[PDB]
Length: 241
Length: 241
Ligand SMILES: CO[C@H]1O[C@H](CO)[C@@H](O)[C@H](O)[C@H]1O
Ligand SMILES: CO[C@H]1O[C@H](CO)[C@@H](O)[C@H](O)[C@H]1O
Ligand SMILES: [Ca+2]
Ligand SMILES: [Ca+2]
Ligand SMILES: [Mn+2]
Ligand SMILES: [Mn+2]
Image (cartoon, rainbow over all chains, first blue to last red):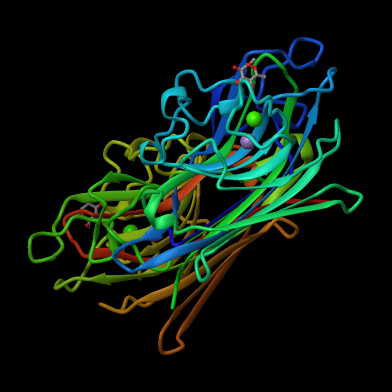
């Protein structure tokens, strides 16, 4: 299809169009990307992801069209500690994507250790909400919590200082305009605190014509829950000047 | 997802979200449901169907909600014969639906011979555009080309006279309003000729909560092409009093 749209106001237990990978599962109307114990508390060493089953036609060579898309979602992070890790990411990748070996902790379940910073070795675009930046393990991170745009590398091409708020839902709007090629990210807490980051990227040179979209999260030594509460997505192929 | 929509202004041969059954396949940016030879001429004894891969949440028991959906599509039929057969149908059925054995010809690839008219043995809602009505073989049909609403039986719960126009596209809008429980059908030819038929049906008593939507077509001894030219669909779960 030229256009596709779907919306999950909440996540009821009986899902049919979601691909669950790793430790991801539905709990209390929300998707728990990372594993939690019987009490509902976060645990260490866990990676989980979800993808919508239907493939998205991001661009079409024959017609020279590129899709304009928008992904709106909200999530919350909770941890008994104060150094919650490692973060959650909205991502777009080839349809057959699977959790790379050794992609836990700071790699957010998106990159393999040996090629995490090799751009010509990856095919992924992600918007990360990174809460752990210890310079000894996450050497590629700025020294502070941040929202970043990742293009084929765990080392963001652009980041913005961000504030982690335990238990508070962050509302996010990610949009891609094929006309200007700008991928814009706007995130806000209920009190109006806003964060914005954007980057110009030609999706045609990074991803194949058909892709799958979803979320990924992980916790290494440090942990926190990564709760996806809602998600709506829409894409439409358009002709650019 | 509570809501889902997709649009196929045309059908490029590079499809990823369509399930093809039988002889259905993409030809010249359109779906040819029934088999055609090298020159694109229709042949006898062929059945074909397509379904969108993502399952649609028609209704939800736990929340007492039922979906409001709309399906807009256009097709054309062509045959050198004076009695082209057998017809095309938009249908809704359980996710695992496959072409029943012996469902060819007048059964439109939708029903099995043994239970074609047994309502307690089927789970399908379809809007048929039936061009073959020979009273000796299609004993259940009125004696003329017609549009029919089928609920668990090849013997339509309702039909209205329809005119078959060789090689002319028919635009159809099928809608279901959960409030009134009305399934409305409106079809038109490019010259303004209009056909309308409506039927009240509680989809909850006929179909499971999750279903797949698509098209089916067949030709027995008499034949014609059944070309799906475009299709858009949208559904949203709504609270029903
Ligand atoms: C000590 O390092 C480990 O734990 C941290 C914090 O969870 C992760 O960032 C890192 O990738 C993992 O290897
Ligand atoms: C002569 O009968 C055969 O051909 C007609 C026309 O195609 C079909 O309607 C029927 O099901 C099939 O058995
Ligand atoms: Ca990090
Ligand atoms: Ca018939
Ligand atoms: Mn980072
Ligand atoms: Mn009929």
